[PDB]
Amino acid sequence: FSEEQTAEFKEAFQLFDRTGDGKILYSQCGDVMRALGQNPTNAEVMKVLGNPKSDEMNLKTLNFEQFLPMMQTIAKNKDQGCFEDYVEGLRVFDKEGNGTVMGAEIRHVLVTLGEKMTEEEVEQLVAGHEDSNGCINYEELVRMVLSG
Amino acid sequence: FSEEQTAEFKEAFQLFDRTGDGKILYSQCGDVMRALGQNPTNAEVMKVLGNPKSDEMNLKTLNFEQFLPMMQTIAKNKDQGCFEDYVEGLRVFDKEGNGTVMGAEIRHVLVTLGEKMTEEEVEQLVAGHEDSNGCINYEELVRMVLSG
Amino acid sequence: CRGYLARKAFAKRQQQLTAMKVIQRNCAAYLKLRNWQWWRLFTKVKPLL
Amino acid sequence: CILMIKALELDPNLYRIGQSKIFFRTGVLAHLEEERDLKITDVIIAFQAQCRGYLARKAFAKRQQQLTAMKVIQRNCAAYLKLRNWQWWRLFTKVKPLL
Amino acid sequence: SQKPLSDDEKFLFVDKNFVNNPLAQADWSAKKLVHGFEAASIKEEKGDEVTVELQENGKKVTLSKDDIQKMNPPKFSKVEDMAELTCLNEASVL
Amino acid sequence: FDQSQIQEFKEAFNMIDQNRDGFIDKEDLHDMLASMGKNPTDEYLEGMMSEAPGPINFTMFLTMFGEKLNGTDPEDVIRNAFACFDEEASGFIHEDHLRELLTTMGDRFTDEEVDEMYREAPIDKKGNFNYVEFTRILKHGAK
Amino acid sequence: FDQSQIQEFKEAFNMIDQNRDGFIDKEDLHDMLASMGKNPTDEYLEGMMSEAPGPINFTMFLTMFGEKLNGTDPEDVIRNAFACFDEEASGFIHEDHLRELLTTMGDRFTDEEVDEMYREAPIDKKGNFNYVEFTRILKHGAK
């Protein structure tokens, strides 16, 4: 992964810095490599970093020299699942395939499938992307979470 | 150190001068050094005086000029009691395991065990802290008398 | 969503960083001038300022 | 247990950090018993002697406090010889009658 | 069995020997306490050429380490479980 | 230095002295601080005046009063970051809030500073440190 | 003002009298200072009471001793500075070099202050003196 957006990577790297030493927490540099044009789960957000433990994740910060390995290991995702597979799979998931999924059931399979997101995570996902119906439209939902 | 306490040394010295001549018995002069903020055991009370024979404890009385070396080695006793040694020796004296030590049990393990002095001494250990079952709050007891 | 929400939370994380960055410096410098030496002998000449 | 093991400066190999007990084979069991017993003696007697002095401390007398008090009297006499003579006893006065 | 109220169990209620002092190494010779063997203190160890201070005999004798095995601290003598000994030699088990 | 501070030090020179010539003398400070309160030992006033070579001269006592009043970041940024640091919604940053900040942020600061600003300032005695007026005290506001 | 000085003034005033009523009553400390030392006359405390608005009350002598010990800072940093002036670390301090360095620093110093210092400094025939007692004396010590 090219060494020219190393500048952008250092930028956003220091963007979610807290120690303030050119060295950024691994969960923090992970949300960094997220908002660098990627969409990784906090799980892979951590694992891409040479697998830092939760201590290393938020205590041993990342020296930017090893953030160049991290930008490599995050640039594998760069985004998440296909939106046609999104729609067909959340249609077949939804018990009818109508076009939306219960905010109940969508927040469910967002906290009951894959990495169990914080319900604030599946909400800032779902809320802010809700249709006020309770069957939160995963189409609008997934897509504005995809762009945002 | 200074004269404000060197005259205190003189006065607390002639305090245990049952002869009132400025020269104080070795047991009584280590008792003086007790009286001077420290607290030597009669054992160390003497021990600071060149390990005096039992008569040198009493007949070779100590003048104030010879009271400065002995008082220095009274302060160098450091047998004022360590609070971890306090709590641990009282903790094996806390054979009841109450964070406290029985008054009768302490007087047993204090004047009928280990180093010796006046029975009243280990009384006013347990006395002034006597409580239920004589359960002298060994931590409270020992921090207070340490400050005391 | 997790990628979405770190993009969403960049806006709070960098501002938290900068805010605490200025906060620590100013609070510490205030406590510094509070432990300054010329504030207990100078504080009686200050009534003559 | 592992803490008091490193405080024993050991680790369980003939004894065992297990799940409910440090199981002891023959060996380290009674050796550690002996170490425990020795240190029990040590700390008991250490507190006992420090407690004899300690109890003289709790025991001093109230002559202690009256002697400290007469020393404070000497201090205050020296203090009145200190400040009431030179002009540092009249350099905050003669104005508060109008302050 | 275990009844201190009845000697009838004290022929089984185990009178595990002891020193009645909080020290545990003053009964077994740190050198070697010593087929009723002869609890002792090695005074001159030259192999088995061990003049144990035969404290059960009072004899600074070059004695067999057959007798001079780990006769564990008599605090572990006459114990319920021989395993309570430091090393279960019949110098102490016996 | 600060122009407002320079004119306030000029005002100082003109209130301590009734014969303004660009120099302050010992008798003026002595008598006036003996009037408002009472001057402490003249040694302390000599020490305050000896922070400048010989008798404190016009620009010289100006800069002397300057470096006696300053030496750390101004009141404005102090009170500003105090405001943006408040996690208590009281208007002033707490003694305990400044306390919990100084430990894990920047460098450590003893509570003796806190007790000193507490006992040596007319702040509100309720466990909250005000800085709208106290920072002006830090620039000669009331004390 | 500072806590240590005022609490020391309080303990001194409480130990000096026999019937404490928040006031310094002539007879009590009169008889005490006569018993241990020089016997004063009622003229001294008569002037002391004419040196205060009405009788000399609690806060009167409180702030009296307060600023009559103010101008002096916490002797912690002062003793830390007094120790490092030595070049061989013998443990004793000399005053003449300090006076020679201060007389060229800032303005010209006075002579009542050095008198106040000398009248309470134990000096031998070789200038032997220490700061363990000097900072104690500057803070209302025991000379």
Image: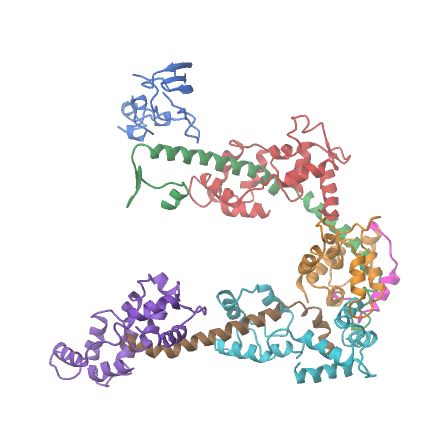
Chain colours: A purple, B red, C brown, D green, E blue, F cyan, G orange
Q: In this rendering, would B90 be left or right of C5? A: right
Task: Please identify the quarter of the rendering in which residue G138 is found.
Answer: bottom right
Q: How many marks?
A: 0
In the image, is residue A107 part of the stretch drawn in magenta? Answer: no
Whether G75 is drawn above or below C29: the answer is: above
| Residue E57 in sight in this render | no
Whether E35 is drawn above or below A107: the answer is: above
- Residue A139, percent across and down? 20, 83
Task: Please identify the quarter of the rendering in which residue B82 is found.
Answer: top right
Identified at 20% across, 73% down, the residue is A109
- Residue D43, percent across and down? 49, 38
| Residue B47 in sight in this render | yes
- Residue F118, percent across and down? 61, 69
In the image, is residue G40 part of the stretch drawn in magenta? Answer: yes
Identified at 50% across, 45% down, the residue is B84
Residue range highlighted in magenta: G35-57
G59 and F60: which is toward the camera: F60
Task: Please identify the quarter of the rendering in which residue G8 is found.
Answer: bottom right
Q: In this rendering, would F92 be left or right of G30? A: left
C14 and B140: which is toward the camera: C14
Q: In this rendering, would E63 be left or right of B64? A: left
Whether G28 is drawn above or below E84: the answer is: below
- Residue D62, percent across and down? 67, 44
